[PDB]
Image (spheres, coloured by chain):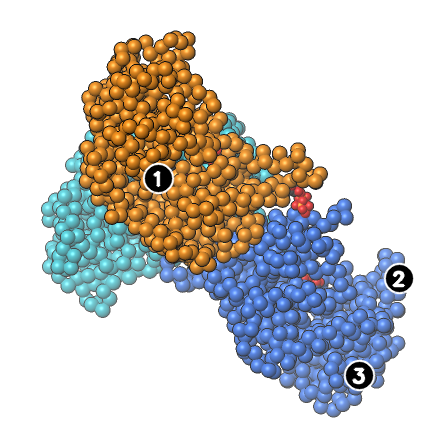
Chain colours: A cyan, B blue, C orange
């Protein structure tokens, strides 16, 4: 096996993940089977305790674990299904060694941070790097290891020990390191010294960088590259630079044009992977398809405006997957994405006396947008405004997607306005009883579950985007579903539930009959959107906002003929 | 409250504990209420998993937890009952913060090594420093904090962060630090540089030493003190030196004569503790009694030779408490202690053909000794030789003490030789059934439990040493007890069980009627031996080995008239 | 005596000098006698070898040494005459200890970087801090020590050793340190970690900061101050911040409003300086006069445009003193300064075919400007264009100042256009002989020398600005003077030499009779411009460019009535 560490810097937030999965997207250009592990220095075992206000969105796996949010950036860049084990955390590894301590697996020795815990970290990395995350069941050929925090933190010290020892447990010419570092510009001059002091830190703990990659406000000057390479064990051609680019999807082409892979090919001696012709071809095809979606961003002539309406939209990382799912789809439509961020509570009739100015800004965004999106918010607060946003797109033929709480609110609105029933509400308003629009179903429902189309719904816009396939597989995070008692009334009035579960009891998709595009999903489709294969419910929202939905379904926008 | 850190060095094993509890023994000379915490960098939560072969003896508390062995050094030096919480460990504190993470006590924040875990360590130190470990229920006035490992270890990095922040959570003029450091002598010259490089390390993590204390092969030269104080923020009078001394019990007088406390009095402004006259007097009396037991070591004219017979006596830390209990008692008898270490298996009739040379060395030790001691060994291996050592002291009137497995073997031997019954054995040889000398009693029996003298046994040598008090309280670690069915036969033959438990079902002490000193205890009395109050079963063993037992009971050897 | 170090950062160029002399300007607000030392890590002994292209202008002392350029920033901020010894450099101190090594002043000991060279640095700082640099001959009360480079450089390591030892040779409560450090803003967030890593570096070498001062793109957030003070031994009120301000002369008011001195008053216990009432008053008056010149910058309604015409004006530090002399004077005139930078060679008739575009930009600047300034350039290259700039201001009544080479070119032009004599040139064109406008006078003439007005010249605009005083004292740097043989012809034609030397042989000032303001000086007056007392030849240039020269001479712009 081969491995690539991405680590480093004098600051957290320097740029690692885009240098990480982006480096891993280019390993796939070579035809390689590829995987990724994110090592987190924080002490949470999982994001299941972490509220979406800090550390952001609880990204959800095929295996239904609430992971680190960043893992998602690797399932889009590489096109892989990761697992709950690919997110190493400081709380996860202290728990695993402490479990073995009380089980007595150390044969009554004292157990130490070195060597026992640093062995555990190496034994975890080489365990997880066997798992076949890729489009065929063979073990990966390269693993990208991203070390979070900064080298020299008292929180990241166990992992730089474990990785140093791993440079020997794995060989040189099988392991390499990319160190990401700061070139601050002050008084209009690029200063090298934070890279010198952080490389002094790096060699102290015993890792040696095979590349340096700079966060800089500028293109690095020719002398700045020379004054970094005069102070580190790299040639001047391995001081990489992730400068300003037209969009984040260009970074793997930027790295490839900086000859980043033409070094890693030699430095990891990748002629030693015995690839079949099918893999070598599928590598070149993935690069061609990347050049196509990238070209479709530069060659983008016209804007699509989408209002994303939810709780606390100020906290923009809390909707990160939703944004990326809209970006992947917008490059298929060749159209520039313009998300309007609406706080759902600013739409309310009460907000007009309380905070009038922001209420007009919110309603201008809703009134301007070519599509509406209710994104699967957290808790009840935003609900009353999200109802009026769903009403706005039901009545006037605006394209719409509701995700999770958005299906809940598409159904509450269609109840509250098409059936009358003005008292109806989420099951969250428990003591109203008779008018609850939803029912509890704890089984929380999580992870990849199937969904099956109802066999008559040949008219459906959404089941056309899925290619007329009989079923789909999707991620879930819900404790409530629409009350089955009401569903015949909603189906008879035209809110047709075009997809249900294995039992047929659970409401998984709705489409409103004879509207240009009004969909909701109980699942979160943004947790399976990929840059070359956009998630179908979000592709339909952008394509109908562009007024091109028919031609996207007919195939006028696939990447290769 | 006031606090004293003891930390440091370029090596583990430099001398901390003797500089720690020894500094704490002198805080008690001032009359202060005193406590101690040992911070261990290892990842075991407790010594209950740790086999006695590495990290040594599982020291046992009043509260019955299997602690770090070193805690014992503080219960002898200070005269305090500690608790399972006074041994902070890296595995204990990661477990406590990870428990709060899954309970959700962090209110859905991400939880970090800084500030959350470094707050947990400070909140633990100031929690535990409230506990009244001393001879009256008031909270301690000084806490001695010993930081294990070395500063600059990747295992000790969380604790030097937590202690730095603690220098502010507690004030300066309430916290002080003693750093213990190496002065190697090579080519006959004292080199200062390992102290310079380790003090550079110390100030990097942000602690500042109020004293330096040197491990050195010599008295520090006047220039060595000056060349350390020219490189650290200490006066030349605060470079302390724990040099070679007549015995370890002299170290608090060495520190006091080096004016170590005459600085800490000012540096911790200890006039601010409002002591009552009773405390001030009991402080001076504790110093006088220390000068007495110390004088009784220098003024020691004659040797007592004791054979300690057990499994794997090569592993001398595995019997550490037993050695210290013999030392405390030997200073009461004014006699020099000479422990002969015997491997119990080398006494066996089989060892004579297998390894004849070591078998003669073992038997010469048994034949020479003025007393025999079977120390409460681990597992079955040594048993056959320990029987012959108990027989040797039953028949010939040699003084004897059996501790735990030693009472078991005193009873197996008295069965195997006085009752005949040559097939009898420990309950460990389970499938013999009918001839098992013991019975299972899991309740493992642990911690401080009472023991009550049988009301007729006024003749007893051991219940005389306990001052004719009605009951005693002692530590236990046993899964087996002598089978109650047999005890009438043993009592009638003269192996009188002079002490039993609350129920009267359990065999806690035996004394053989009409022998000069042949005792065993099911408890481990070495876990309550103190330097001014020696544990009575061990005092009797030394005093009878000295042939002075009568006069020790009559009071010819108490420290003050 | 008291002392203040200014040091630090993860980068060179962070802001030290403005935090240094600015802190020293506020020590003078307290009435204190004040001095400054700049410690340079570079190996040049003096700027006399350093070409003005790199490290910039060779600033010149009262004592005529070619110093570090930065010393000037302290002679403006404090109002002091420094000496060649106030610029400590790595080349200067290795030379001084190596001289004592060959003289044998070490009594045949081996001489070491510690302690001998670190003693030399301390013995230099306390030597120089005695020198009476101030407006009365008493020794200074505070010394500001600026440590150049960054802490943790292999070039600055001898000085952080010497300063650590100096924290003891001088007492605490006599020495304090200000550490200047970076808060980079990326992704719109202020990151603290470069300050944590550089403070870890600082405490390693053993200095402790009594203040931190941040270079930041922003006002520091309340949490950024707290997260620095949680990681350093400073209160949150001693994390100072030199943010963006209207001009550099506001920084001492910014520091004073951040309560910077209200701490240093206590931290250096400055009630212990026994000031007389005259000093206490002159302190408050200096603050009032600073508030006045600062107010005159904010209250500045109208611009003055000045063309500064010379060689290589792209290298803007090479003219630094000239810029500051124009700034000090512009605040007296209440007018906003706008220096147009002209490359002198772009004015040439040859430049019109060679590089036409830049030639028009150069001539637009010359044609726009309200005043012309020829700044005392280095070498011959620019001369031909500087002639045409002097002609432009002779003929059309534009205000003019020529400094050094500018007097040379004022005289070459007046010769070349008023006397005819079109072949005349600088003595630099040696082999023309008969038409050389100048003569060699090596004595190089350097340092503070007098100049005496010619006793009839009561009409003079410049000798009016000097207050009708009989003589002036000024800095020089010249190897050529105007040929005395010609001076009668120039005086008779109206280029009156209104000032000459002690002998009357040397051409020190000229004024053209009956022009609104056309001055030149052979000396460099910008080496004695101060912020409260602007250098008179530059005050006249700004005031005549403003058309207000009469009223400045009559006194309509002095700071206090
Ligand atoms: N392939 C990627 C990589 C990053 N991002 C986005 O960029 C931001 C985070 O970038 P990252 O690469 O993780 O840098 P930071 O986290 O800011 O810093 P670090 O280097 O510490 O990860 C987030 O919006 C993340 O979703 C993304 O959309 N796609
Ligand atoms: N010396 C330190 C300081 C912090 N941490 C931990 O590592 C993380 C790094 O986060 P970082 O972005 O460094 O936060 P700050 O320390 O505030 O750094 P910044 O100021 O850039 O946020 C911290 O959250 C904390 O978990 C650490 O290990 N060692
Ligand atoms: N009051 C004390 C202190 C120490 N010792 C003994 O000395 C040895 C350990 O000494 P210690 O002070 O702990 O030093 P080390 O552990 O060798 O090193 P460190 O400084 O790391 O603790 C053990 O036999 C311990 O029982 C003792 O008998 N009584
Ligand atoms: N931090 C230090 C200390 C000393 N030196 C210099 O390097 C030499 C090393 O000599 P050394 O043997 O280290 O002398 P000491 O510092 O006293 O070390 P030791 O105590 O082993 O003599 C010193 O003489 C002094 O010249 C140095 O460069 N850096
Ligand atoms: N009282 C001052 C201080 C500084 N400057 C100007 O500001 C620049 C240099 O600022 P300085 O304070 O020296 O910062 P740097 O040299 O950039 O960085 P350092 O902190 O390393 O000195 C130069 O134009 C210098 O003349 C000035 O005009 N007046
Ligand atoms: N590790 C180093 C590197 C350089 N220097 C010296 O200290 C000076 C600091 O200048 P600096 O501004 O740090 O130059 P760079 O090293 O290039 O840093 P920058 O990239 O910010 O210019 C250097 O010129 C060199 O004299 C040093 O002492 N130690």
| Label 2 SS | helix
Q: CA distance from mark 3 to mark 2?
A: 39 Å
Query: Which mark lies nearer to you, 1 or 2?
Result: 1
Residue C317 in sight here: no
The answer to whether tags 3 and 2 share a subunit is: yes
Residue C530: numbered disc: 1
What is the secondary structure assignment of the residue under circle 3?
loop
User: Which residue sits at x=65%, y=49%?
Assistant: B194
* CA distance for labels 3 and 1: 91 Å
Which residue is outermost to the front? Answer: C456
B69 up-or-down from B419: above or below = above
> Where does label 2 land, which residue?
B360
* Host chain of mark 3: B
On screen, B477 above or below A55?
below
Q: Chain of mark 2?
A: B
Q: Is residue C495 left or right of residue B157?
A: left
Q: Which residue is mark 3?
A: B556
């Amino acid at each position: 096996m081969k491995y690539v560490v991405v680590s480093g810097g004098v600051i957290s937030g320097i740029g690692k993940g885009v240098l990480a999965s982006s480096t891993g997207m280019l390993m796939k250009t070579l035809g390689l089977k590829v995987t990724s592990i994110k090592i987190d220095p924080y002490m949470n075992i999982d994001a299941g305790t972490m509220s979406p206000l800090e550390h952001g969105e609880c990204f959800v796996l095929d295996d239904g674990g609430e992971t680190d949010l960043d893992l998602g950036n690797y399932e889009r860049y590489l096109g892989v299904t990761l697992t709950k084990d690919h997110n190493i955390t400081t709380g996860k590894i202290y728990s695993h060694v402490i479990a073995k301590e009380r089980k007595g697996d150390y044969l009554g020795k004292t157990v130490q941070i070195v060597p026992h815990l640093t062995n555990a970290i190496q034994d975890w990395i080489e365990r997880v790097a066997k798992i076949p995350v890729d489009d065929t069941g063979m073990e990966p050929d390269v693993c990208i290891i991203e070390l979070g925090g900064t080298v020299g933190d008292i929180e990241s010290a166990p992992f730089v020990e474990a990785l140093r020892q791993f440079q020997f447990k794995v060989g040189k010419e099988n392991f390499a390191l990319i160190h990401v570092s700061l070139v601050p510009v002050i008084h209009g001059e690029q200063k090298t010294k934070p890279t010198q002091a952080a490389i002094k830190g790096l060699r102290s703990l015993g890792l040696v960088p095979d590349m340096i990659a700079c966060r800089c406000s500028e293109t690095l000057d020719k002398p700045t590259i020379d004054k970094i390479a005069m102070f580190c064990h790299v040639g001047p051609e391995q001081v990489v630079n992730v400068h300003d680019v037209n969009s984040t999807y260009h970074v793997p082409l930027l790295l490839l044009e900086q000859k980043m892979i033409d070094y890693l090919h030699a430095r990891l001696k990748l002629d030693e992977i015995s690839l079949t012709e099918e893999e070598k071809q599928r590598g070149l095809e993935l690069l061609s398809k990347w050049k196509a979606t990238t070209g479709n961003f530069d060659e983008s002539m016209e804007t699509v405006k989408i209002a994303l309406v939810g709780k606390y939209t100020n906290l923009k990382d809390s909707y990160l997957s939703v944004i990326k799912a809209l970006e992947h789809s917008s490059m298929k439509c060749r159209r520039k994405l313009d998300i309007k961020w609406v706080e759902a509570t600013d739409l309310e009739p009460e907000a007009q006396e309380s905070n009038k100015t922001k209420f007009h800004e919110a309603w201008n965004m809703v009134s301007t947008a070519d599509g509406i999106l209710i994104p699967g918010g957290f808790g009840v607060r935003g609900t009353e405004g999200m109802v009026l946003a769903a009403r706005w797109a039901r009545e006037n033929h605006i394209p719409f997607l509701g995700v999770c709480l958005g299906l809940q609110i598409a159904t509450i609105e269609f109840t509250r306005s098409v059936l009358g029933r003005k008292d109806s509400h989420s099951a969250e308003f428990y003591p109203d009883i008779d008018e609850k629009n939803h029912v509890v179903v704890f089984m929380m429902r999580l992870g990849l579950r199937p969904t099956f189309f109802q066999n008559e719904t040949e008219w459906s816009q959404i089941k056309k985007l899925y290619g007329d396939v009989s079923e789909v597989h999707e991620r879930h995070r819900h404790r409530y579903e629409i009350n089955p008692k009401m569903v015949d009334e909603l189906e008879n009035n035209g809110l047709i539930f075009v997809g249900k579960d294995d039992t047929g009891k659970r409401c998984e998709i709705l489409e409103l009959k004879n509207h240009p595009y009004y969909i909701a999903t109980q699942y979160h489709p943004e947790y399976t959107s990929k840059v070359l294969d956009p998630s179908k419910p979000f592709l339909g929202l952008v394509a109908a906002s562009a007024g091109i939905l028919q031609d996207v379904i007919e195939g006028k926008y696939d990447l290769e003929a």
